[PDB]
Amino acid sequence: GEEQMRLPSADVYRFAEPDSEENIIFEGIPIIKAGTVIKLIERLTYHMYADPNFVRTFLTTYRSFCKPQELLSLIIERFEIPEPEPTEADRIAIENGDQPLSAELKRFRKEYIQPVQLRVLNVCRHWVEHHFYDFERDAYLLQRMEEFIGTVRGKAMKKWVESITKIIQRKKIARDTFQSSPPTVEWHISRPGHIETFDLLTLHPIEIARQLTLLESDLYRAVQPSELVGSVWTKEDKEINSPNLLKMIRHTTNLTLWFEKCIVETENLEERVAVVSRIIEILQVFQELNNFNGVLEVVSAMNSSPVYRLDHTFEQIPSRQKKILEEAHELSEDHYKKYLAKLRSINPPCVPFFGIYLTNILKTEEGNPEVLKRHGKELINFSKRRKVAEITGEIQQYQNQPYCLRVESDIKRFFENLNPMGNSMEKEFTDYLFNKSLEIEPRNPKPLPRFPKKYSYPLKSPGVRP
Ligand SMILES: COc1cc2ncnc(N[C@H](C)c3ccccc3)c2cc1OC
């Protein structure tokens, strides 16, 4: 039909085949459900209208179905559009040295070529702006992008080229505040600079919670949405593709296991009650700071196999502290209902519980297929990627909430360098912790033995009041 005859032939251009039930399906601007990578590229650079939601979602999630080098190749191929031949009358005009009318040729340039080409430059611009890490990770990808952008011709295009170049140069330069005064840094037994004595009971619990909240706030803010798409952090190139997400997970493992280690390696019962009570006070200060992540790390250490079973320890923990722990536990019950309302009801700044996003992303990744099948043809399941992208969007809404708290560089380093496992792998460390729990508090038929004190300093806490 007339509309399809004015588009380029399939023998000269791959992005103009007619839409069909076996190359694209959909759920204002229509919402793409699934499609071939070629039909996804066509709609990413659609001539009829701009589509900021699809562009944003595509560039966050495309790595789960297309490599960066392949995407750049596809948008460059999209950009090189063949022009139609002159009409018979215009061929005669050209043959006589005269100017052709070129009525359809001019219509095709203005209504299809120029919009698609600007749509391609818009993808390039959004790509360099929001996902510059693709270019930092692949210097050759950036070389290709700059060669492409640098050889575009025309005045309306050179302005787009300049704004794309401006972002690229700003991103390269980038790689090579508090309204109120922050509260005074709290000290307890350990003195500033005496890093050799830093420990759970020697540092002030207020300061432990404040420095862990700064650390976790920074780890939470550094996570980029694409590190969470397609379970790439659990796959071969995880270190390159999910460096910030892996640091976030490693910190929670290390901190959680260090709390467990602090507890079960305190073999004396009265000393272990002081350790458990101190971790609960740390949790209370995380609650005051709206560090839900920290609260649920403490809940996770208290609920772990080696700690949860310590009946004699928890028996000496005051009811008030047991009630705080129970209420913190109940943040997680009923698919995190209390937590979700508390996250929305509190005033910023805060650190959301990161684990819930990973759980929801993994359920979406496992619960939906990679492709949809329509008339024997496989189509990329794009709605699956959009659902994952919507969860990463929830992560991003809390990533601009800095804390009015002073960094204590030695305490920061102390928590950044937690290494409870040492040369052990996680399984043999958790097996060791559990066996240590059986040693300090044997199962009921066996009696409770006594163990000598390991701490020379006082056990009384300075409390959670500044
Ligand atoms: C049925 O399983 C549970 C129910 C719980 N209900 C309430 N609080 C819990 N944990 C908090 C952190 C806590 C409270 C006091 C002492 C030790 C830990 C629960 C933990 C559970 O199992 C892992």
Image (cartoon, rainbow, N blue to C red):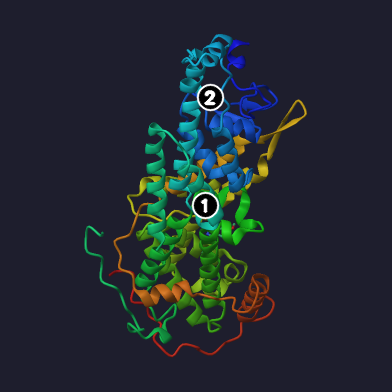
Q: Residue furthest front?
A: 96
Does residue 28 show up? no
Determine the image quadrant of residue 40. Answer: top right
Few, some or many residues within 10 Å of mark 2 (<14, 14–19, 20+): few
Q: Which mark is residue 143?
A: 1
Q: Is residue 342 shown left or right of residue 255?
A: left
Q: Residue furthest top?
A: 89
Q: Is residue 365 above or below residue 98?
A: below
Q: Residue visible at 41% across and 34% down?
A: 157
Q: Is residue 417 above or below residue 131?
A: below
| Total labels drawn | 2
Determine the image quadrant of residue 462. Answer: bottom left
From the image, tell me which residue sits under label 2: 30
Q: Position of residue 47 (x, y in %)?
A: 50, 25
Q: Position of residue 360 (x, y in %)?
A: 57, 47
Determine the image quadrant of residue 406. Answer: bottom left
The front one of 246 and 270 is 246
The front one of 149 and 137 is 149
The front one of 358 and 17 is 17
Helix, strand or loop at label 1? It is helix
Amino acid at dot 2: Pro
Answer with the quadrant where ligand 1 appears in the image.
Answer: bottom right
Q: Residue visible at 50% across and 79% down?
A: 272
Tag 1 or tag 2, which sits nearer the N-term? 2
Helix, strand or loop at label 2? It is loop
Q: Position of residue 151 (x, y in %)?
A: 48, 41
Disc 2 to disc 1, C-alpha distance: 35 Å
Q: Which mark is residue 188?
A: none
